[PDB]
Each structure stands twice: as structure tokens, then as C-alpha cells.
Image (cartoon, rainbow over all chains, first blue to last red; front, top):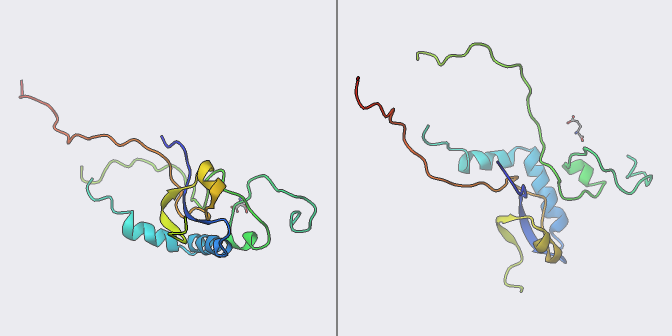
Length: 49
Length: 51
Length: 49
Ligand SMILES: N[C@@H](CCC(=O)O)C(=O)O
């Protein structure tokens, strides 16, 4: 079973001006279904049985 | 609405992070993964076809 | 150390790393598993007897 459920993040320095816009551009891509496309073309293959 | 209207500091509960809320409120790191799922009744007799 | 303005990689969100850098909202929710070897089925039936 899964343990230590911590996601993948885009690290930046604490003084970065992009932190607000980067997170919003990730949440938008989650709702738009963009990150499900990146799942399809890269992660969801299933190859054999 | 309570946090936006200054009536409270935090809003702990089942609040899902999305884009439009996060532009009016300041969320935290998710403590549990959620999303959108479909709940359906259990399928009836489903022996694999042509077995 | 300034050698990179961002980290775009499978970098999990951690307590220690969060003190020094600011992660974005996760772009992939996952956890820790264990990878082990597998066997192809054989039915292990020596003969009809
Ligand atoms: N959990 C949702 C409300 C229920 C739904 O998904 O419709 C939210 O926090 O906004």
C-alpha cells in the first residue's frame, strides 16, 4: 500500500516572484485536463497484460 | 466567504484547492488527495466474454 | 546556490526541503511503493496423471 503520500512539486527559491503564478498555472492545468494528457502520453501505457 | 469577508482566519475542512478560490484565499499544502470520481452500482454477472 | 532558478523534476514535497525552498502545488500525487520481481504463469501441472 502507498505510504508517505507526498506529491511532486516545482521547487523555487523563497524569494522567487514566479511562485504565485507557477502554482496557479499548475492548478489550471489540473482542471483543464492538461495534466491528464501528460499522464496519457507518458504514464498510461500498461504495455502487456 | 468567511475567510474572504475577514470573519475567520482559517477554514479547515473539506475545502478543495482550485484556481478561482486560490485567487481570493490562500490555501495550504494538501493533506489528502481528492478530485472528481464517478460512483456507479456494482456490475451484474460478468464472466469474461468467449472464455 | 544560484546554479538553477527552478527545479522541474519528480521532486517530492518534504518538510526539510520546504524550510529552504518553496514548492509549488503538486503536479502529481503519488506515494512510496515496493518493486519486486514477477513470474509468468505456468500451471505447474507435470502430466495428466
Ligand atoms: N468538496 C467540494 C464540494 C463538493 C463537490 O465536490 O461538489 C468543495 O470543497 O468545493
